[PDB]
Length: 135
Image (cartoon, rainbow, N blue to C red; front, side, top):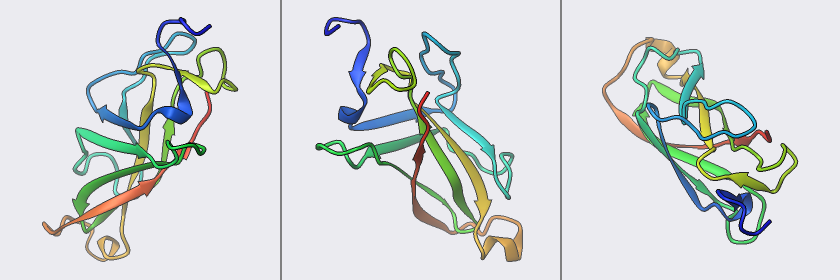
């Protein structure tokens, strides 16, 4: 229904700001951290971001295509990343619950980082094109 509280069309979400110490909203599932390191060849004990911004590159009429950019040591990159929001009524819903979106990322060594296995102190801007998980 068009007055259903906290109901938003996923394809029209333009951007996200995700915090490591905040939880997602959830009605059907279970709140999770908005921003979570879930693995990687460098592990989640290396530097981890506290906030990540993601843009929906298809917000102006197309399917969702999340791009999440940050600055990391040149030793590191994001591996696979996954954005996921809670479908309002089900995982098949094109409407999602406001506040329910979150990012999971893996923190890998780059091919240069694998040579050294520690931080260089030099940084690079890096963008991940996330896969989307329907839930």
